[PDB]
Length: 193
Length: 187
Ligand SMILES: O=P(O)(O)OC[C@H]1O[C@H](OP(=O)(O)OP(=O)(O)O)[C@H](O)[C@@H]1O
Ligand SMILES: O=P(O)(O)OC[C@H]1O[C@H](OP(=O)(O)OP(=O)(O)O)[C@H](O)[C@@H]1O
Ligand SMILES: Oc1ncnc2cn[nH]c12
Ligand SMILES: Oc1ncnc2cn[nH]c12
Ligand SMILES: [Mg+2]
Ligand SMILES: [Mg+2]
Ligand SMILES: [Mg+2]
Ligand SMILES: [Mg+2]
Figure 1 (cartoon, rainbow over the protein chains, first blue to last red):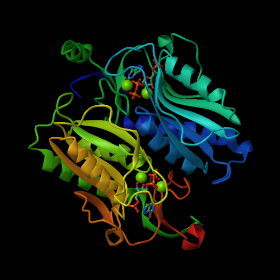
Figure 2: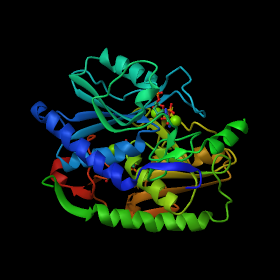
Figure 3: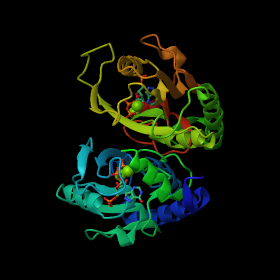
Figure 4: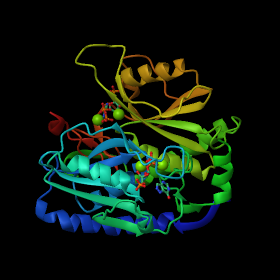
């Protein structure tokens, strides 16, 4: 990728880490007696970014016999830009109630944590049986508000990453690898506005 | 797979076919001058079933250097027997306007085609540079309204399939393979 400063994780690496995280989620939830139809683990996939991670994660979870039920929601905060708007917009909420069910919010990245903080708070008041979060990437040095996900596949430095569902101006979501976007590429693009 | 009466496609067979379809889409768009930001191929992923197909397809398209823009839409039924035009309530629509853009609607399965036909014409009215559809599975014999998808990964018999995004009672979407649900189970 000529627009990439560097590749952080290859597709193979992500796949490996996701399987390991799935095995852990499976072990941690064993006592919950998850069962299809009556007791699935509800995966709240945060669109658009989480589509890819969710697709691969639910499969890895299936490998470990963890039955799941997908709920796709859509939340917006960065829009076409590089930084948090400071506002988290709910564009689509869950189709069904989460009350009394085990819920795992599936996110591609946590940076300032405004998104996950807003989401966790919203669902928390809905009284699910349990509420946890799994993030693909944790940009630890990017927090504006505190938040610690229950499961983290990878930690990354303070650089704008793209690929594997993550975008910059709704571009690059389709990359198989996670890469650092060159500032000369986003600067030119940002300049175009 | 005790709940399945037969295996239709394994994850590896699906993976392969998707790549062949992506290579074709790429060739068919080679003369569209597609470029990121300004002229990407807009994939309108119809939730919830196509989320998995969309994830692997966009990656296959990326293998062929096609710049894509992902859109996810959520539709709902107005009520029972309130239409036959396949009209659906739009709970979540495209973020960007498709007007003047090359669009590809992504679906997991087409059978009756009532909803997909409705969606096709709806987006068609928004005036995109072009509009095509790609469906992973097609029950050609199930049509309730005439409809032909532009790209299809596999034609299948009239049996209820699950897995690879497809569900039954919101169950089994996470399967890596596409299997036929034991008719008894479906009831
Ligand atoms: O921790 P935060 O600073 O809140 O940043 C993380 C959020 O920002 C991104 O979403 P975005 O708002 O870009 O929407 P998107 O998923 O559709 O790309 C990313 O997908 C997370 O949802
Ligand atoms: O062509 P037809 O026989 O009418 O059916 C096709 C539609 O039904 C299914 O969606 P569903 O209503 O099941 O929504 P879902 O994708 O969220 O499961 C499938 O995923 C297509 O959207
Ligand atoms: O590095 C990054 N890439 C894509 N989206 C986001 C959001 N926060 N931080 C990001
Ligand atoms: O076989 C099938 N499996 C899952 N959803 C649908 C819709 N129509 N036909 C289906
Ligand atoms: Mg997001
Ligand atoms: Mg974004
Ligand atoms: Mg569907
Ligand atoms: Mg369904």
